[PDB]
Image (cartoon, rainbow, N blue to C red):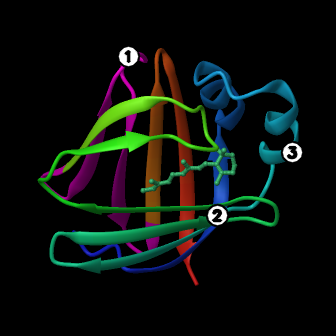
Amino acid sequence: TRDQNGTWEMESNENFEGWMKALDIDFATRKIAVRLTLTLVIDQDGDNFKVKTTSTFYNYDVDFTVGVEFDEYTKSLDNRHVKALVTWEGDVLVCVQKGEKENRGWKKWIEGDKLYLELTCGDQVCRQVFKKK
Ligand SMILES: *C/C=C(C)/C=C/C=C(C)/C=C/C1=C(C)CCCC1(C)C
């Protein structure tokens, strides 16, 4: 299904550290964030997405429209300018962030009652799994 609406609680996080390191997130921030349980709140209406990523210490928000390129400044993440584009490949939602880092972006999809998120940067892949709250 393409329906990713919901409140999603993290149950698994693979190689989060390797991915953050590939983005050059500073050593001290990584120590805090690496084992936090993340919650994703996704509001999806047609192409319009509002995604909130929350944890005890860090709260992020991004809004986008599927099919519409948007320039992003990655703020409290790695502080870079990228050109972002989110599209569908079948029922996989694919984000490409063009800029300095190669292979930068993510893919999100649903299997049963679970949301899967694959984050990529350089040669690093982080895989996260969430259950619907
Ligand atoms: C569609 C799912 C998306 C866009 C989720 C993106 C998640 C992040 C950019 C997460 C960033 C971080 C936190 C919320 C705290 C943990 C460490 C960070 C900085 C990687």
Kind of residue indicated by mark 2:
Met
* Numbered disc 2: secondary structure: strand
Please name the residue that numbered disc 1 is placed on.
102
Calculate the distance from the C-alpha at mark 2 to the C-alpha at mark 1.
26 Å
| Residue 100 seen from this side | yes
Residue at image point 43% right, 18% down: 101
Is 72 on the left-hand or right-hand side of 20? left
Q: Choose mark 2 or mark 1, whichever is in front.
A: 1
User: Which quadrant of the view contains residue 111?
Assistant: bottom left
Q: Earlier in the sequence, mark 3 or mark 1?
A: 3
Calculate the distance from the C-alpha at mark 3 to the C-alpha at mark 2.
16 Å
* Residues rendered magenta in the picture: 87-114
Is 28 located above or below residue 66 in the figure?
Answer: above
Please name the residue that numbered disc 2 is placed on.
10
Kind of residue indicated by mark 1:
Glu
Is 18 on the left-hand or right-hand side of 131? right
Is 43 located above or below residue 72 in the figure?
Answer: below
Residue at image point 18% right, 45% down: 69
Is 85 on the left-hand or right-hand side of 23? left
- The majority secondary structure of the magenta stretch comes to strand
Residue nearest the observer in this picture, 92 or 70: 70
Please name the residue that numbered disc 3 is placed on.
32
Tell me where residue 44 appears, x and y as whole percent: 29, 77
* Numbered disc 1: secondary structure: loop
